[PDB]
Image (cartoon, rainbow, N blue to C red; front, side):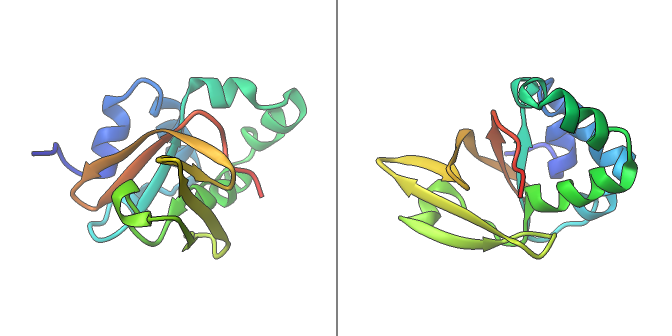
Length: 135
């Protein structure tokens, strides 16, 4: 049935919680605050813990550096596992492209595997990632 927007799902999950904090601090909430089509990759606790001391100390210290990276985690095209097929060039809200592919029934974005895909929301889809997406 679903609950609400992608934001509603992200706050219902303990792993997406830190992402909600980044989204809030960067000011990206207004994007997911609208209904339509979106594909959000939400990093888990492991992803944020795997972040290097140098990078995560810098990135999480500035709202603008946060906002920039968040725009790369949100795709502008809804591609679920059953919709991808083999490989698709998905555009992100940053302007760059996410190389999302499905091979051996394993979905991966920029080589990074998805932990739990095809999370249905009212305004798009959410793909759980255990890694962060860095250009």
